[PDB]
Structure formats: structure tokens, C-alpha cells
Image: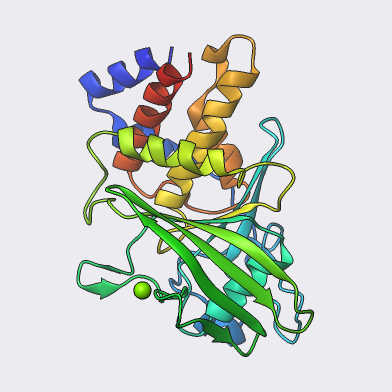
Length: 281
Ligand SMILES: [Mg+2]
């Protein structure tokens, strides 16, 4: 199965129809806090907000808002934090979240600049000797090492909480080759990226949830966790053909709006899972 559906939707050409049905059935929940006037500058897009019920709260109060959601997958025993690309004014808040939630990894699925426009602040240091200090949230960030490969980069970062003096090692997994328009033609490198993040331990229960983002934190970000979770379920269940990707997507959409932004992203999600399932045997 799944193959059968993918093949049928392809030859019938009904990806938009299938995808619009998902948007129709998707959950709606309030975003009261996001839409507060004081949080205008904390949101990259006006149509992408975290639900109040699943929003991640910062502890350093006065303002606890950040555009990020906890996607908690019960059956798969997997949690993710999906968030927007940090803004110039929210880089401190982002590393505060990473700290307070005890995350081990940050997964980044966008370039800083795409289509001639800045889609993300430069929130991590690029030279070892030029560390970053975030004074508002009181954190120091140092680049420890960098490993540039053809489809992705991995960085070891050191996050220091300056008020306690504790330090943590954070792994930055940066997927660099997602095309400016649409989706990749083969999911091979995206899957190799997924398995590389898995292999680090960054998705395991011992740590806080992985922090995942693209620009809006719903498109490519949603593709990443949808594929991961579907692939887990196929390992866990008796009869792995019971895994319905649309149902899993609707479950994730209970926790964050607009996950999977296009019908090509849906098609690609299917494609990744199918091929990813064939690798694990
Ligand atoms: Mg150097």
C-alpha cells in the first residue's frame, strides 16, 4: 500500500484535490497570544502562528512569547519543536528556548538568503574566534567545529548559560540544498540527512525535543517530522502498511497550523517515506 495510492494520485493527477482536503479537515485552535500587538515583531509571517495550547513558553517572563510549537506524537514516542527562522530581534529568544527545553539539536532546512531575500537571521557564529553574546537572554554561543558536505553541514556549537556558567554541546544540522522553488527531485539526500540527525541522538528521549525550522517553520519543517514519524511507525507496528500519512499529517496539524505548504510538498513527503521504508530492511 501507499505505493498504490501514490501511483493512483500520479496517473489521475489529483495532488491538489488530496491536499485541499487536508487543509479543509485541518484543526483550527486559537492563537490569542501570538496576535497580541506586543508580539507583532516576534512573528515573521502574519498567517503563521503557534496555537495557544501547544506554544512553547519562554521562562524569562515579561514576555514569554516565541513563534514555536511542540508537536507531541504519542504513538511514535517522538517530540519536535517547530519554529520560524529567527528574526533579528528573536535570536536571543531562540537560544533561550533551546536552553530551557534542553534540546540537543537544531535542524535547519533553509539558507539564510533565498530568492534574493533574507529568510532567516544569522543566529550562529561562523568563525571559532568570533563568538556571539546574546545580552537580553544572557547566553554565549561559540562555534566549536564545522563539517561541510555536499548536501548538508554539521556544526558543533557550545551554548553557555552566563548566569549559571553551565555549558552544553548543541549540534547544528543544516540542510543546504533544498531548491529555491518547489521540492527536490529525489528524496535521497533528504533521507540521508534525516538518518544523520537520528544517528546523533538528537531525536532520542534522553534529550529535550529537537528544534526544527525553515523560514516559516511549517513547510520543509513539516516534511522533516512527517517523514521521520511515518518511518518510525512503520518500524513499530505489525503491518506497516497501516500507516496512513494523511492521518499522521492531520495529527501533527493539531499542534501547528499549515504543516506541508504545497501539494508538491505532500507528494515529496509521500515519496520520501516510501523510499525511506525500502532502505530499512
Ligand atoms: Mg579559521
